Image (cartoon, rainbow over all chains, first blue to last red; front, side, top):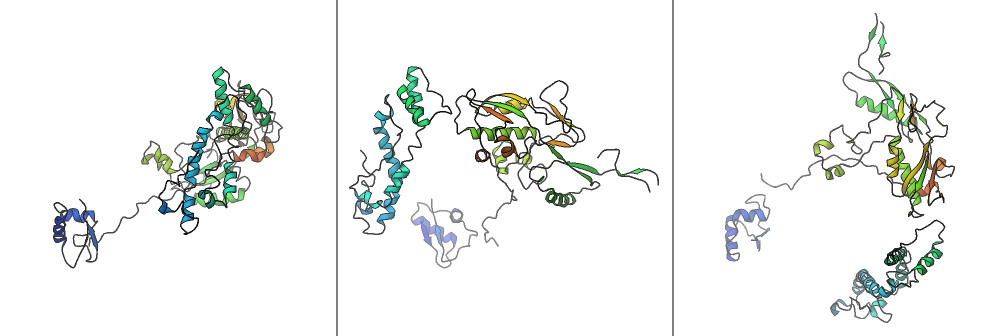
Length: 53
Length: 135
Length: 258
């Protein structure tokens, strides 16, 4: 999955939206590890995240 | 007989199309040329096998230098500007005629004798036909 | 340095300086062309490596003696005629590295392919060009030096076209410095105090190519073929000048953890 962030949804909130179409969503740590996040809140709202399983 | 690999591709790539109707036809049709001559060497060398393993050998000529495309074909028309130059570097096979002296050493080994050692006073053209009639 | 002249000085009575040595320089074929260029570079180097209580007092340069070395090579039966310039280059190269002790240098990553660790590679001083893990074990230049050539024949027997050698001698070119053959053996010769061997000076054009016979190749019984100067240099192994860059760990991607 590729996801477009929008304005102050957290990583804890965005990793719950992956569970709609990923058969049990990715954890908010393992979502941050796959994208190579420097921080848990280190995403700009324009950035595209990727959620593989 | 050799049938080209550029025939079996789908016709939207344009290899059997009319020549240079679109500009992308010519850089594609030169890309299939090195992988065609590698396969055309494989089809010659099976047809050379009665010549390559005959006991009455008479030739310098080994693996092969024939052009892959028939002269009427559209595949010949693409590289018609450098077909004289490509056939002449295909005549590097005469430089590989030392290999023919290693088969005569192998074919003489059926009858228990090795080939002669190479000397310094050979006159290597006239040396070799003596080695050929010996077999 | 020799103990008899060790910077002894009066003004009161006799006082000898402890701690300054001499070095003997055996220069190569290149630097004997230009002695003055190698002199200014070594005098720069010894101040940068001058130790705590020691210094160089006297520098000794060495003088060549051409060691003529008749040796009659017999070639194999099934060599090609075009491989014979490969033979003349080969019998020259294994003759040099035995008589002239040359240090072998090669790259770090070649040593990393080998079994020895990273502690063994960087053991000596910092070498900008190559690494020298084995020394050529150079003989001292306090005394005169024997050169035993009975070990040479298997180094000469090694190469592919060579089946044996027929002769090993010198044609009276040793009398200029009175090189005496030691007690009974024909192979050894002892060069007098200062000199070092130069076996064939200006080697291929002066000696090997001219068919005067310092080295006589015998091929197929008697045909006895020869070669010119430039033909063997193409089949000669050409060395490569290698420089060793410093080892660093490159940066990773900087992450905004702050």
